[PDB]
Image (cartoon, rainbow, N blue to C red):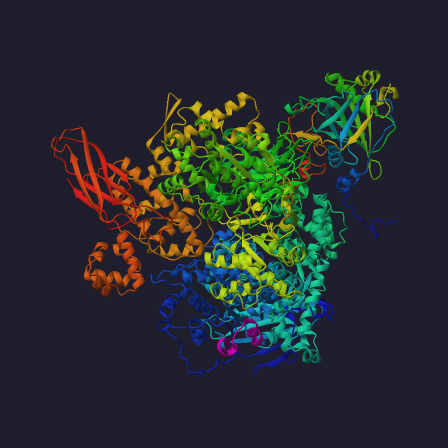
């Protein structure tokens, strides 16, 4: 019983700083990237992901809050069943450990008009056997709103942080999963009606043979996880040909600098 | 390198107490001193001394008895004081190094004045003016505030001389501008050390003639090793230069001054003066209070009690100045004293009741805004420290000088920077917090001396009173220091590794022996010899090592192993050699300790975030004594969990506190702990240069992310803000409330660019700030970017970046320059493919700037690169341009070479012709495989031929095959041989004279550039050798010159040079020879010789060679096999990279060519000698010595004494020659011949001779591949054509089985050389950038009459073929026929438009074109159309000879005149009386150099060998520029300027000013002979001819040979009788034809070319007949003529009336003075 003999005082211990020290070391994981290859048939398309933009995507991410990129690409001159991923587009976004939050507006720029959309890629805190129902809902709603997203051609690549490394698995929606994700409003962990036959693995290879590139917003940066207020599902944005800053860069958290200066 | 050494422990030799070390053990006080006792403190009193009565009976020297140049420096003084009077002779009448020891304040800086005045006097003209650009004086002062006071007072005493005195400042690039205009630099030791550490190019350090070292007793401080480094470097450099530097040391009176004097090279008998403490201006009665209480509370109580009692002994009677040692302590003790005065009712003693000073105090207190100053000023107490306003501090100073403030508490700053004595001084404690030491420590000796020096006002008091209060156990120390007994020691050991690294990085120390020598100049050395016991040496050690040879070797060995462990130096323990490194260089140049750069090298990685960057910084060894104290741990913690950059370490670690302190300094937080605030100041005072070292490290490694974060952090440190803040904050004049309103408005800065003042004021919600913010927005630096991508191959890409400034300049904001980095980053923004510095000068703030560079590229092409241009000092100031490759068109991969066929070696007998075979059969028995493969085609057909093969393939014999064939077909057949270099053409001329004139008795000629000379040469000769421009002037007029059409053979050598800097003239003349061949239905055979070309097929197609006649050999087929080695050196500083090449040069000789001859190419004249000497130095310290000499020493003594360069004699003796532009051609011949014969084995050649070198070698080494261009002030890459020419010198077919070449280059060039020396070379046309003068000539000759013709013209060029093969290079985007048509049309349009605006041509119906007058003048004299335009825009109907010299010296033909030498400033100061003068002077401009060298020529002034060849090039064009002016004037009817320009032609020919004696033309006439002839009254050349022979012999006073030269000139002098007749003179009819026929008769037929020795080219006599009228100055007619024995000439005019007019007739020379005739009619 010490109200007076023993007195202690709380000292702040903010979490984003531990996550920032953690994200400084993401580059170690880019020398240990693995792809799941449990899909066997090759009946679907084969998706080739250039390592350069993969590694940059990993480097700009966070270990807890998910980030997403849009995939754009084409089939090689004589091989229509192969989809080369040529561009990853970063749009104003914010996220949690389970999902990402994107604007309704898909990328629009002159440089992308000769490519076709191939879906999206997102980081994940832990490896999973199945595609998330959040992901099935996200992909299905994007498809219902944007007809340029062929369900038989657009994929979800998941990039899971496994110890010391990164595991990549690629999925697509099946018709049943499209029709379920469209109407799904419970985005808990197990919503009504969710099914494993709603998605399927698509084959996916990492390549060193060609290089991808990034496009990023023209006025802002992409990371709004420190500004989630100023993010609006209807926000409009343009794009430029430039490489994205990393998660905890100064331009993503200007209040940490101005508010410390005020003290 | 004496082996049995030992590794010492430097730390155990260090004097730990710094300036507080007390070497003396006993202390003796003046007579009359005594101690008193009191409870817990002892007092020692020392009485004021009496002045030494005059013993030497030396009266004070009156200013009037000084030398008169020195008297203006003593204006307003009557006589020097006693010290200056005893020093006057040594200071003013000798250059003897001095050491003056005198109590602080006795006159020492007036002695330094006298020294500076001696130096100033050395540079005083007869005009009274001073050559302020002929010298510099360095004044080294310990404290910055002292530096500033000295700048003021020295500038004020020396104003009357026009001397600038200034402080050296922190900015590194733009300040050297002012440093050029500063004659006296005042700086601290450390700043002069940093400056002379960088060394480098464009240094004014060479001008330094006098260094003053004030307060040289700083030697005893921890800063003392800087002074040792400075003096040792200065004295060794005096020896390396033989240029003297006077050293003046000013010291307090302390023991070991005899050793200090030894260290300064002061003769004790002549330059040492010691004045004891009795020479203090005001006698000093000293009181020392030493407190014994060890309890802190009681001790500070006791201190305030002693202070109060001492103050009460002076209250009302004397001012009291109390020094305390922090800023807060000034107010704290002022308030302590004031409170104890009010508690004791004593405040009334300081201010008497009703004093006007009491009211002045109340007033200024109420007006003052310093709250401490407000609280204290009414009582007569004040504070003074750095943290106060300048107006506040000026108030305190003025009110203390005014006897108003009776108690002033202050810091050391006031004692150093301001002049303010007080009757009483109290030093309150001697304890100070040193962040560097991390703890409390005793005050520095310098601070104490200065502070106590402030007691006693000089002309108001009769005694000062200094009271020092300290710990009892420090009494002896302070008693020693203030009573002449604290010995000055050396602290050098503590800094030995760092100091030594500086001398290694500078090249001054290359091995341990050098380092032992260097340490022999240290003050450390002199103390070690005089007092070995102090420095860890036993007296037995010394008697065994009397010069301390071994001890110095051991110290140097210890230091070297430390530097080597830290990777700053590569130390070969066996040899003792020292190899510099990039880390070592950065450590020296950013003034960083060697442990710190080891840490940086160990921790920095490309993946570093801001987090590890701040940590890496916080681990610097500058901060190794910083600790986290318990009482800081709360405040630190409050900040640690709020800093925006996370910290991984606990706050128990010093590194975490240092990191937080940086982050708080940037956020501008005010801290509370006093320890914390002083630590933060120390940590951030050095963060900028430490972080700028990180920047340089990571930028030069190509790390793009870290280069961005590190430059960013430098700028946040310097601007005191984060990126995240409004960049508008960087305008200090902008009020902070507004910027914070805007930062709250939060919108992106960039959108402010697209709003006008009104919408600005709307978004802000402040309307007036609308216009102010608009202005600042557009003052913010901003650049627009665009690229022209130019593929070179499929893997190398040239980029042209255009930088367009997009902001308003304002010198208030931007200064006079703004600096940027251009960074070329790859697809991923991870690698800097290329970077460079870019300086936008205020001069050019509105002009576009062009940058060109190369980047590698690959297949499959990457999506894009990025070009970042980022400000070097502005935060948030950057532009990035994506460079996409989605539409890059690559050139087709280049073809396989022509197979080298294994033919049997072709015997000389193949030529089937004994006369032809006599050319070669002595030299060799068989032609090489290339000659053997092309022989059948060259010799046995008339097919056009292309031969491509490396230099040294024998391609000139291939040309000889075609000439021999021609000689068989046509007995008088004509071959024109074009080579692009004049020195190449002169070598070819000697060899082909020997082969084809002496042997075959054909006629060989070399074109000279004189059109009538060259027409006769082209007529008579069968082999005409020429450079391109000489053939251009000729063959432009081919329609009217049958000899240009009747050319049988056209050979062009080194044709790959179409792609280089002078390629367009070569492309044009080759296109012209093809076009003439197609006109004349009898084709001209062409043979092109080239280096290996990747696009050889394109050259061959352009010249009409079939595939079977195109021999496209690649470098692997050189008949002497070449072994090429490319060594990269990863040093980005040029001087240091050359130093690191020095031993590799020697090692390359011994590896690749230890017995056979070696040629070393170096980038400049200076380096040739330096590298010769270094090769000899390395030879001597090696086992093989003099191994390069093969003639005996006595065989080449006759050779040696014929040379004037004595260093060249010395090095030649040891087997090493050198060649540079500055040697007399005979010296070059002597060295070249000693090399050819084998006497000497190595020759060090300047890069600029690589085309006219007439020797070859087994091994060529190219030492660096860049050279400094003094016009653009930057390093320029060697053109690849020069490198191939250099490499071609490693080729000796008759002697060697192989050639060897080593190219030593900066590492960022290695890839490029491997690409463009191992593979054949792609060449492009640059004719589309040089079209105007060729289009103009073609419109003059009617080859182009319209725009369609101009397109058809272009189709004949190599440009036109390469546009199809590489469209992106010529800024085409497709190769379709209509793309090509459109591009050609636009080129034509742009060029005819420029011509027509320049009034060179006319354009009728926007279709037809026709030559105008100016265009015909440009074409005829082969002058740049812009020159002729400028002539039309500058010449007037009244212009004079000075105008003419200005006009012609500003012609375009002189912009490329070589620039470097700085005696131009000396000729410019002689231009105070140069006969003709104009206006402003610049020293860099090539046009001003040409104007100066022209005035030097007309005034027969002998210049450097370099300036001599420059004058020769200028004179090579002056005559035709003058004739162009003459035609411009005569076309405008202006008579006076036309005749003045005919005179100016005369003057430049005969080297002669406007009005001299015509007798100045005669050989061997001096001033005396002209005086004598004028005395007899002859004044004329014809008068010399008229004299009776013996009479003129008795007059001349001249040799017989000299009289005969006079006679040869007098026979060749023009002797012309003219007679003129006006035809039809009877019938004067207005408006009609006036025919004047003038005849010219020559008394003695011409006997040769003009006699004009001082003119380089050989001229022929030229005349103009003018008929202008003088009254109206109307040039009426004119006709130019060449005269043999007799000639008739017609002049046309159209009458003005039937008014019986009057005209003057002029017959005017262009070559001789005196022979001009005037008549009238
Ligand atoms: N390289 C060098 C040039 C000048 C000096 S100085 N200013 O000491 O004489 C020292 C070194
Ligand atoms: N680390 C490093 C430094 C400088 C250079 S260079 N070749 O630009 O000078 C290369 C590597």
Residue B16 rendering spot, x and y as whole percentages: 69, 68
Residue B589 image-quadrant placement: bottom right
Residue A190 rendering spot, x and y as whole percentages: 87, 24
**Relative horizontal placement of residue B1670, taking residue B302 as reference (left or right):** left
Residue at 28% over, 35% down:
B1531
In this view, the residue in front, A228 or B828, is B828
Residue A195 rendering spot, x and y as whole percentages: 88, 20
**Count of picture labels:** 0
Residue B739 shows in this picture: yes
Q: Is residue B1623 above or below residue B1170?
A: above
Residue B224 image-quadrant placement: bottom right
What secondary structure predominates along the stretch shown in magenta? Answer: helix
In this view, the residue in front, B303 or B629, is B629
In this view, the residue in front, B1227 or B1571, is B1227
**Relative horizontal placement of residue B1216, taking residue B572 as reference (left or right):** left
Q: Is residue B1227 above or below residue B1434?
A: below
Residue A263 shows in this picture: no
Q: Is residue B466 magenta?
A: no
Point out the stretch of residues depicted in magenta: B257-278
In this view, the residue in front, A80 or B285, is A80
Residue B543 rendering spot, x and y as whole percentages: 68, 80
Q: Quick one: quadrant of the C terminus of chain B?
A: top left
**Relative horizontal placement of residue B562, taking residue B1481 as reference (left or right):** right
Residue at 48% over, 28% down:
B1354
Q: Is residue B266 magenta?
A: yes
Q: Quick one: quadrant of the N terminus of chain B?
A: bottom right
Q: Is residue B1188 above or below residue A188?
A: below
């Amino acid at each position: 019983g010490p109200l007076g003999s023993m007195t202690q005082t709380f000292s702040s211990k903010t979490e984003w700083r531990v996550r920032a020290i953690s994200a400084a070391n993401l580059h170690l994981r880019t020398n240990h990237i693995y792809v799941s290859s449990d899909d066997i048939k090759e009946t679907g398309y084969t998706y080739i992901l250039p390592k350069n933009v993969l590694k940059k995507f990993i480097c700009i991410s966070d270990l807890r809050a998910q980030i997403a990129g849009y995939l754009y690409g084409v089939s090689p001159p004589d091989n229509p069943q192969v989809k080369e991923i040529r561009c990853i587009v970063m749009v104003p976004q914010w996220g949690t450990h389970q999902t990402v939050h994107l604007p309704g507006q898909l990328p629009q720029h002159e440089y992308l008009k000769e490519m076709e959309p191939l879906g999206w890629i997102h980081t994940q805190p832990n490896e999973s056997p199945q595609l998330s129902p959040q992901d099935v809902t996200t992909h299905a709603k994007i498809m219902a709103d944007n007809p340029s997203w062929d369900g038989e051609k657009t994929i979800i690549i998941t990039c899971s942080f496994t110890p010391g490394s990164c595991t990549l698995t690629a999925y697509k929606l099946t018709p049943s999963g499209y029709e379920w994700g469209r109407q799904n409003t419970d985005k808990g962990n197990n919503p009504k009606g969710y099914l494993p036959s709603h998605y399927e693995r698509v084959q996916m290879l990492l390549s060193d043979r060609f290089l991808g590139f990034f496009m990023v917003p023209a006025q802002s940066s992409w990371n709004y996880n420190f500004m989630g207020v100023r993010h609006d599902p209807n926000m409009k944005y343009e794009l430029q040909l430039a490489n994205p800053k990393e998660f905890y860069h100064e331009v993503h958290r200007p209040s940490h600098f101005l508010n410390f200066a005020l003290l | 390198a004496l082996a049995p050494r030992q590794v010492l422990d430097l730390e155990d030799l260090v004097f730990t107490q710094g300036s507080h070390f007390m070497a003396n053990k006993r202390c003796q006080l003046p007579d009359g001193s005594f101690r008193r006792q009191r409870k817990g403190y002892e007092e020692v009193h020392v009485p004021a001394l009496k002045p030494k009565p005059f013993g030497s009976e030396e009266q004070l020297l009156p200013v009037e008895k000084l030398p008169k140049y020195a008297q203006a420096g003593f204006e307003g003084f009557k006589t020097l004081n006693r010290i200056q009077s005893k020093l006057y002779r040594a200071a003013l009448e000798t250059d003897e190094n001095l050491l003056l020891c005198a109590p602080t304040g006795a006159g020492k800086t007036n002695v330094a004045l006298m020294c500076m005045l001696r130096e100033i006097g050395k540079h005083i003209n007869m005009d009274g003016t001073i050559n302020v650009d002929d010298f510099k004086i360095i004044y080294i002062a310990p404290m910055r505030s002292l530096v500033q006071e000295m700048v003021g007072s020295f500038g004020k005493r020396l104003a009357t001389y026009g001397i600038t005195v200034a402080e050296l400042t922190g900015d590194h690039q733009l300040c050297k501008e002012e440093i050029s205009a500063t004659q006296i630099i005042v700086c601290t030791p450390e700043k002069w050390d940093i400056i002379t550490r960088k060394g480098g190019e464009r240094t004014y350090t060479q001008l330094v003639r006098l260094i003053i070292l004030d307060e040289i007793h700083l030697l005893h401080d921890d800063r003392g090793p800087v002074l040792e480094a400075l003096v040792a470097r200065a004295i060794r450099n005096i020896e390396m230069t033989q240029e003297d530097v006077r050293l003046i040391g000013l010291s307090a009176t302390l023991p070991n001054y005899e050793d200090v004097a030894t260290f300064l090279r002061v003769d004790p008998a002549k330059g040492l003066f010691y004045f004891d403490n009795s020479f203090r201006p005001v006698p000093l009665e000293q009181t020392y209070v030493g407190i014994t209480e060890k309890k802190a509370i009681k001790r500070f109580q006791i201190m305030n009690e002693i202070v109060y009692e001492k103050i009460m002994e002076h209250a009302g009677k004397n001012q009291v100045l109390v020094f305390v040692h922090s800023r807060k302590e000034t107010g704290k003790t002022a308030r302590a004293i004031r409170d104890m005065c009010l508690e004791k009712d004593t405040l009334g003693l300081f201010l008497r009741e009703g004093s006007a000073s009491t009211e002045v105090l109340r007033t200024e207190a109420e007006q003052c805004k310093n709250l401490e100053l407000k609280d204290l000023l009414p009582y007569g107490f004040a504070i003074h420290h750095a943290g106060m306003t300048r107006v506040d501090r000026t108030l305190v100073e003025d009110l203390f000088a005014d006897k108003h403030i009776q108690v002033l508490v202050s810091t050391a700053t006031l004692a150093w920077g301001v002049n303010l004595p007080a009757h009483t001084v109290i030093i309150k404690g001697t304890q100070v917090y040193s962040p560097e030491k991390g703890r409390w420590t005793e005050l520095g000796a310098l601070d104490i001396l200065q502070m106590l020096g402030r007691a006693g006002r000089p002309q108001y008091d009769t005694k000062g009173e200094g009271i020092l209060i300290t710990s009892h156990g420090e009494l002896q120390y302070y008693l020693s220091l203030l009573n002449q007994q604290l010995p000055i020691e050396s602290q050098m050991v503590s800094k030995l590794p760092d100091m030594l690294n500086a001398e290694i990085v500078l090249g001054n120390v290359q091995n341990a022996k050098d380092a032992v020598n260097w340490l022999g100049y240290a003050y450390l050395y002199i103390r070690m010899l005089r007092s070995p016991t102090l420095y860890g040496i036993s007296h037995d050690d010394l008697k065994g090592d009397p010069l301390l040879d071994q001890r110095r070797l051991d110290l140097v060995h210890t230091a070297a192993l430390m530097l080597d462990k830290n990777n700053l130096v590569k130390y070969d323990k066996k040899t003792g050699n020292f190899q510099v490194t990039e880390l070592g260089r950065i450590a020296s140049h950013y003034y960083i300790t060697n442990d710190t750069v080891q840490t940086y090298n160990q921790l920095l990685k490309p993946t570093l975030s801001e987090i590890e960057l701040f940590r890496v910084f916080s681990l610097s060894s500058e901060f190794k004594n910083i600790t986290v104290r318990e009482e800081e741990k709360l405040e630190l913690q409050k900040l640690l969990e709020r800093v925006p950059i996370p910290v991984k370490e606990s706050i128990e670690e010093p590194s975490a506190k240092i990191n937080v302190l940086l982050q708080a300094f940037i956020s501008q937080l005010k801290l509370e702990g006093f320890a914390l605030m002083a630590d933060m100041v120390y940590v951030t005072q050095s963060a900028g240069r430490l972080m700028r070292a990180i920047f340089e490290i990571v930028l030069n490694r190509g790390w793009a992310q870290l280069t961005d974060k590190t430059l960013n952090l430098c700028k946040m440190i310097d601007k005191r803000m984060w990126q995240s803040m409004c960049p508008l904050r960087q305008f200090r004049k902008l009020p902070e409330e507004v910027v914070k309103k805007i930062e709250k408005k939060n919108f992106p800065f960039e959108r402010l660019y697209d709003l006008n003042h009104n919408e600005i004021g709307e978004l802000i919600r402040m309307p007036k700030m609308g216009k102010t913010i608009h202005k600042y927005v557009h003052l913010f630096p901003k650049l627009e970017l665009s690229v022209h991508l130019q593929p070179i191959t499929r893997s190398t890409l040239k980029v042209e970046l255009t930088i367009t400034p997009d902001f308003q300049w304002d010198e208030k904001v931007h200064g006079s320059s703004e600096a940027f980095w251009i960074l070329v980053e790859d697809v991923d923004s991870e690698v800097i493919l290329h970077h460079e510095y870019f300086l936008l000068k205020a001069k050019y703030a509105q002009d576009e700037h062009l940058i060109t560079f190369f980047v590698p590229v690959f297949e499959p092409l990457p999506p894009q690169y990025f070009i970042r241009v980022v400000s070097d000092r502005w935060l948030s100031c950057e532009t990035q341009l994506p460079v996409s490759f989605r539409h890059l068109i690559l050139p087709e991969k280049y073809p396989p070479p022509t197979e080298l066929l294994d033919l049997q070696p072709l015997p000389v007998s193949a030529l089937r012709n004994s006369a032809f075979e006599s050319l070669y059969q002595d030299k060799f028995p068989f032609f090489n495989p290339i000659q053997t493969q092309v022989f059948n085609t060259v010799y046995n057909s008339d097919d056009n031929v292309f031969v491509g093969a490396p230099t040294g393939s024998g391609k000139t014999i291939c040309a000889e095959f075609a000439i021999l064939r021609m000689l068989l077909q046509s007995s008088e057949g004509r071959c024109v041989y074009i080579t692009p270099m004049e020195a190449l053409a002169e070598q070819v001329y000697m060899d082909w004279y020997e082969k084809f004139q002496d042997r075959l008795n054909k006629k060989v000629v070399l074109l000279t550039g004189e059109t009538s000379t060259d027409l006769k040469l082209l007529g008579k000769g069968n082999i005409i050798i020429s450079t391109p421009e000489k053939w251009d002037i000729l063959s432009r007029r081919w329609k009217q010159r049958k000899n240009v059409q009747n050319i049988n053979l056209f050979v062009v050598d080194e044709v790959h040079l179409i792609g280089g800097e002078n390629g367009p003239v070569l492309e044009v003349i080759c296109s012209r020879m093809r076009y003439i061949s197609s006109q004349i239905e009898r084709p001209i055979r062409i043979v092109a010789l080239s280096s290996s070309l990747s696009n050889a097929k394109d050259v061959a197609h352009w010249l009409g060679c079939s595939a079977t006649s195109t021999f496209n050999f690649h470098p692997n087929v050189r008949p002497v096999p070449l072994e090429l080695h490319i060594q990269g050196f990863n040093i980005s500083h040029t001087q240091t990279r050359l130093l690191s090449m020095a031993k590799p040069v020697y090692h390359a000789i011994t590896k690749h060519s230890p017995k056979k001859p070696v040629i070393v190419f170096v980038p400049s004249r200076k380096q040739t000698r330096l590298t010769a000497i270094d090769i000899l130095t390395t030879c001597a310290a090696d086992i093989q010595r003099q191994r390069f000499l093969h003639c005996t020493e006595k065989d080449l003594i006759p050779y040696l004494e014929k040379l004037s360069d004595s260093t060249l004699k010395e090095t030649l003796l040891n087997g090493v020659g050198y060649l540079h532009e500055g040697l007399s051609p005979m010296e070059r011949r002597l060295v070249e011949q000693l090399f050819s014969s084998g006497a000497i084995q190595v020759v060090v050649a300047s890069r600029s001779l690589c085309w006219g070198m007439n020797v070859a070698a087994h091994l060529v080494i190219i030492m660096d591949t860049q050279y400094y261009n003094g016009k653009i002030h930057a390093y320029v890459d060697y053109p690849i054509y020069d490198v191939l020419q250099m490499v071609g010198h490693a080729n000796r077919p008759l002697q060697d089985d192989e050639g060897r070449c080593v190219i030593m280059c900066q590492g960022s060039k290695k890839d490029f050389f491997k690409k463009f020396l191992y593979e054949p070379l792609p060449v492009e046309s640059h004719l589309d950038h040089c079209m105007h003068d060729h289009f103009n000539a073609e419109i003059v000759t009617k080859t182009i009459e319209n725009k369609q013709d101009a397109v058809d013209y272009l189709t004949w060029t190599f440009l036109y073929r390469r546009m199809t093969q590489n469209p992106n290079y010529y800024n085409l985007q497709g190769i379709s026929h209509r793309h090509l048509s459109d591009h050609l049309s636009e080129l034509v349009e742009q060029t005819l438009s420029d011509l027509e605006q320049s009034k060179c041509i006319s354009i009728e119906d926007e279709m037809d074109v026709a030559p105008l007058n100016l265009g015909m003048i440009a074409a005829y004299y082969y002058i740049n159309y812009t020159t002729i335009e400028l002539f039309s825009m500058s010449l007037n109907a009244k212009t004079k000879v000075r105008g003419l010299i200005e006009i012609i010296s500003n012609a375009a033909e002189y912009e490329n005149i070589p620039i470097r030498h700085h005696e131009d400033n000396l000729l410019r100061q002689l231009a105070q009386k140069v006969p003709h003068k104009l206006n402003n002077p610049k020293f860099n401009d090539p046009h001003v150099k040409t104007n100066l060298l022209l005035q030097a020529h007309l005034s027969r002034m002998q210049l450097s060998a370099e300036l001599q060849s420059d004058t020769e090039e200028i004179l090579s064009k002056a005559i035709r520029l003058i004739q162009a002016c003459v035609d411009v004037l005569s076309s405008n009817g202006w008579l006076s300027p036309a005749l003045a320009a005919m005179e100016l032609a005369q003057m430049v020919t005969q080297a002669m000013w406007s009005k001299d004696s015509y007798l100045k033309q005669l050989p061997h006439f001096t001033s005396e002979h002209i005086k004598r002839c004028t005395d007899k009254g002859v004044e004329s050349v014809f008068d010399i001819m008229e004299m009776e022979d013996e009479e003129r012999n008795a007059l001349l006073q001249l040799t017989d040979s000299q009289i005969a030269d006079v006679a040869r000139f007098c026979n060749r002098y023009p002797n012309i009788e003219l007679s003129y007749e006006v035809v039809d003179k009877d019938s004067i009819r207005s408006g009609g034809p006036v025919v004047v026929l003038v005849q010219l008769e020559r008394e003695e037929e011409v006997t040769g070319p003009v006699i004009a020795p001082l003119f380089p080219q050989k001229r022929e006599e030229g005349w103009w007949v003018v008929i202008g009228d003088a009254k109206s100055n109307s040039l009426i007619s004119i006709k130019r003529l060449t005269l043999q024995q007799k000639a008739k000439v017609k002049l046309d005019f159209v009458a003005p009336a039937t008014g019986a007019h009057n005209y003057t007739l002029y017959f005017m020379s262009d070559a001789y003075m005196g022979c001009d005739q005037e008549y009238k009619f």
